[PDB]
Amino acid sequence: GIVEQCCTSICSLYQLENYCN
Amino acid sequence: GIVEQCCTSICSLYQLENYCN
Amino acid sequence: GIVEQCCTSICSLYQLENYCN
Amino acid sequence: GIVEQCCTSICSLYQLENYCN
Amino acid sequence: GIVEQCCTSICSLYQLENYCN
Amino acid sequence: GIVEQCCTSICSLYQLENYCN
Amino acid sequence: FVNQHLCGSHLVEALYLVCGERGFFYTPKT
Amino acid sequence: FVNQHLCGSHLVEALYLVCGERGFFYTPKT
Amino acid sequence: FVNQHLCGSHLVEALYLVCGERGFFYTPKT
Amino acid sequence: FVNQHLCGSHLVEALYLVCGERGFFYTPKT
Amino acid sequence: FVNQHLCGSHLVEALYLVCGERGFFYTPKT
Amino acid sequence: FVNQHLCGSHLVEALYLVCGERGFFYTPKT
Ligand SMILES: [Cl-]
Ligand SMILES: [Cl-]
Ligand SMILES: [Zn+2]
Ligand SMILES: [Zn+2]
C-alpha cells in the first residue's frame, strides 16, 4: 500500500492522490 | 509574490513548481 | 467536524482517536 | 532517557507525558 | 514569556538559545 | 553542497546561512 | 493529555501521532 | 514533479498537501 | 491536486515536496 | 493509543502535543 | 540570523534546532 | 549553538529559520 509505494519505495505526487477520498 | 500569495490567498502546486531549480 | 473543531475551538487527543482506522 | 525510551526504543503517548513539566 | 513573545511579536534565535539546557 | 555539509555530514546554524540569498 | 488547537497539517500530524500503525482518515468539511 | 521517499509524518504531510480538502486515508496496514 | 493555503515554513515544506531533487528558491518579499 | 519511534524534531512535536501548556523538558543527554 | 515569528509547535521546532544536543525546556504561560 | 544532521524537509525548515526573509536556495544537486 501507500507505505510500500511511497516510503519503502518512491512515489509521485500524482500517486499520492491515489489516497485522497 | 509566491510567498505572500500562498499565505494571503491561495496557491497551486503548479505555481510552486515555478520555484523549483 | 474534527478538522474545523480542532482549528476553530479545541480538540482532545481522545476525539482525534475516533479518526484512527 | 527520552531518546532511548522514545526514539531508540518505542514509546507511548502516556510515556511522553513523563517529560511534561 | 518566550513562547508568547515569539508568537505575539518576534523572537531572536539568540533569545531561544536561553532555553537550551 | 548543502546536503553533504548538513545532512550527510553535520553543520552549524551559521553554515546554513551560507545558503541564504 | 491536554487539549489541542490544531489547524492545517498540524491536525494530520496529531492524527499521525495518535493513530500510528492503524493510521486514520482525514476528512475536512468541503 | 518528482518522486521522493515519503515516510511516516512526512507521508501524511504530503497527503495533506496533495489531497487537502478532498481529505485522505492514511492506512499503513494497507 | 487542490489549491493550497501555505504560510511560513509550510510553504518551504510544500516547495520541498514539489521540487524534490531539483530543490527550489524560497524568495519572500522583504 | 500506540507506540511509534519518535526521534529528533518529531519527538519534540509529540512532546508538544502531549504536554502542551504544561510544557516539557527535552533533555537528550538524559 | 533573522528574527522569528514562531507559534505553536514551530517554536519547539526552532528550539530543537537551536539547542540540538543540550535540548531545552519549553515553558509557556498557563 | 550546535551542529546536527539536517536532512530533507528538516534541512529546508532550518534554512527557513536561519534565512527567513533573506530567503534561500535549496539546491540538493549542489
Ligand atoms: Cl499554522
Ligand atoms: Cl526523518
Ligand atoms: Zn504551522
Ligand atoms: Zn522527519
Image (spheres, coloured by chain):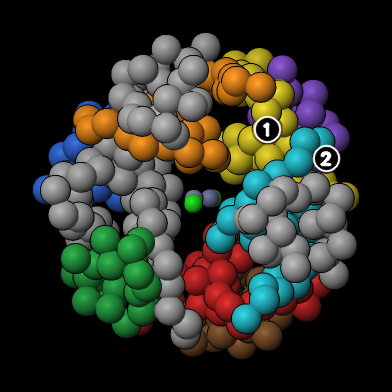
Chain colours: A brown, B green, D purple, F blue, G cyan, H red, J yellow, K orange
Does the residue tagged 1 have its C-beta within 8 Å of any atom of ligand 3? no
Q: Nearer the viewer, mark 1 or mark 2?
A: 1
Q: Which residue is labeled 1 in the image?
A: J20
Q: Which residue is labeled 2 in the image?
A: D12
Query: On the rendered image, what quadrant is the C terminus of chain H found in?
Result: bottom right
Residue J15, relative to residue G5: is it above or below?
Answer: above
Residue K27 position, x and y percent, is 59, 19
Residue K16, relative to residue A8: is it above or below?
Answer: above
Query: On the rendered image, what quadrant is the N terminus of chain H found in?
Result: bottom left
The residue at the point 67 percent across, 28 percent down is J21
Residue H28 position, x and y percent, is 75, 70
Distance (Cα) linking label 1 and label 2: 16 Å
Q: Toward the viewer: B19 or G28?
A: G28
Report the side of J11 relative to D10 (left or right).
left
Report the side of F12 relative to K24 (left or right).
left
Q: Secondary structure at mark 1?
A: helix
Q: Are marks 1 and 2 on the same chain?
A: no
Residue H11 position, x and y percent, is 58, 66
The residue at the point 35 percent across, 74 percent down is B11
Amino acid at circle 2: Ser
Q: Secondary structure at mark 2?
A: strand
Amino acid at circle 1: Gly
